[PDB]
């Protein structure tokens, strides 16, 4: 599913992401925009052989099992394919674990490079929330 901007914001808000660990909703929408272009089915392979999955491009080296990343962990305890669903619940729950692990949203390279230090509230402007 390809989300609309305000549609995704409302879904993220409903799943408890707004101000989660101090990150306002705009940060999460900005990260999803530049990680996946709001597409739940996005996948991208990394040089180390791991793969990033879903709207927040969660990585198979640490967070999910895709059966082809040798010596990887499965810290969100889920198949990576579950992260590609039109229902974002699994992606959201796993993201909460990631952002809590010490490094905050810096774990998402696109957030660090394209959202951090910008007017992220602009991403939810005009939305009915
Ligand atoms: Cl915001
Ligand atoms: Cl393969
Ligand atoms: Cl694996
Ligand atoms: Cl959803
Ligand atoms: Cl933080
Ligand atoms: Na894994």
Image: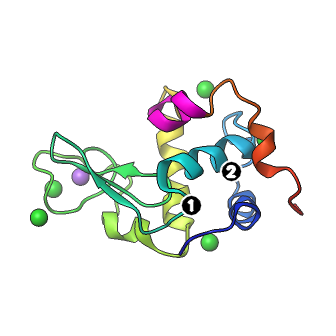
Q: Report whether 129 appears left or right of 92.
A: right
Looking at the rendering, which quadrant does residue 62 occupy? top left
Q: Is residue 75 above or below residue 82?
A: above
Label 1 C-beta lies within 8 Å of the nearest ligand 4 atom: no
Q: Which residue is mark 2?
A: 17
What residue range appears in magenta?
A: 106-114
Badge nearest the viewer, 2 or 1: 1
Q: Report whether 114 appears left or right of 126.
A: left
Q: Quadrant of ligand 3?
A: bottom left
Q: Report whether 68 appears left or right of 15.
A: left
**Residue 115, position in %: x, y?**
62, 33
Frontmost residue, 111 versus 92: 111
**Residue 74, position in %: x, y?**
28, 52
Q: Which numbered disc covers residue 29?
A: none
Q: Is residue 108 visible?
A: no
Frontmost residue, 74 versus 91: 91
Looking at the rendering, which quadrant does residue 128 occupy? bottom right
Q: Is residue 114 above or below residue 6?
A: above
Frontmost residue, 124 versus 129: 124
Q: Report whether 53 appears left or right of 111.
A: left
Asked whether residue 109 is drawn in magenta, I would say yes
Q: Which residue is mark 1?
A: 38
Q: Quadrant of the C terminus?
A: bottom right
**Residue 85, position in %: x, y?**
46, 74
**Residue 89, position in %: x, y?**
56, 66
The secondary element bearing badge 2 is classed as loop
Q: Kindly report the secondary structure that dominates the magenta region of the rendered protein.
A: helix
């Amino acid at each position: 599913k390809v989300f609309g901007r305000c549609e995704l914001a409302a879904a993220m808000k409903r799943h408890g992401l707004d101000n989660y660990r101090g990150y306002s909703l705009g940060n999460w929408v900005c990260a999803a925009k530049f990680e996946s272009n709001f597409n739940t089915q996005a996948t991208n392979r990394n040089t180390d052989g791991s793969t990033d999955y879903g709207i927040l491009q969660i990585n198979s080296r640490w967070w999910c099992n895709d059966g082809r990343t040798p010596g990887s962990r499965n810290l969100c305890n889920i198949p990576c394919s579950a992260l590609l669903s039109s229902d974002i619940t699994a992606s959201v729950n796993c993201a909460k674990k990631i952002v809590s692990d010490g490094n905050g949203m810096n774990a998402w390279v696109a957030w660090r490079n394209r959202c951090k230090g910008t007017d992220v509230q602009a991403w939810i402007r005009g939305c009915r929330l």
